[PDB]
Length: 20
Image (cartoon, rainbow, N blue to C red; front, side):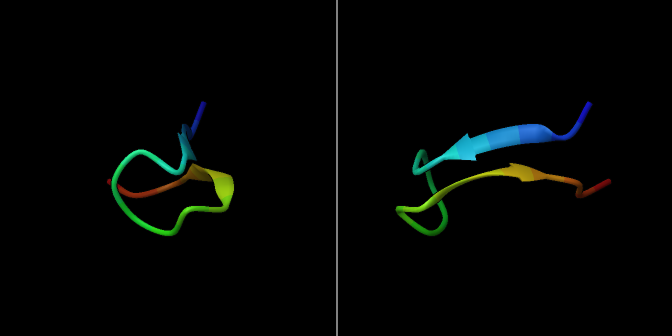
């Protein structure tokens, strides 16, 4: 599963990070 980026580092907006 993509690393849900809940405003951790990138955009404040939470969203799964499907980056290899």
